Length: 89
Length: 89
Length: 9
Length: 9
Ligand SMILES: [Ca+2]
Ligand SMILES: [Ca+2]
Ligand SMILES: [Ca+2]
Ligand SMILES: [Ca+2]
Image (cartoon, rainbow over the protein chains, first blue to last red):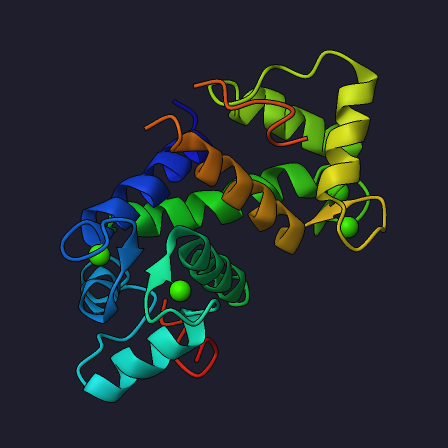
């Protein structure tokens, strides 16, 4: 009901929208990660139009080295975005 | 404009609403943290009505040990909340 | 949804 | 606000 609580539900809701598309329903594979970014982060990140950007992003976010982005790794990605957003500001 | 982007702005907006109240405008002191929780997380966390809960929460979130909760430590707190939210579910 | 407090800490 | 990509990585 508060805007922060709305933010918490959004984080959960969007991760699962994408993670559940294919394979492990609790992790984002590259194609799921790419679409999440392109569809849902278009005001903060440049549309990914090259395979190697998809690959490099996953390499960066894939902290435990299993080829996918789990929810912990996703939150780290969100922390990275949110931090980078101020600054600017 | 997407709900995830809304979530990213909310995270920033609410942290600064509280962090800027007193002292260091970039960190939450105990009283700022307590009000953030009580005012903005009332559907996920029990209202803090005892000094020692305030103190223990700060002790937990204060990773670099400077007595305050900075934005990095705040995101960790959000990660903790969001993770705990499924499960349930 | 109370998600709380020892969980957490 | 493009926040991107090397920043990031
Ligand atoms: Ca998946
Ligand atoms: Ca992984
Ligand atoms: Ca402050
Ligand atoms: Ca600290």
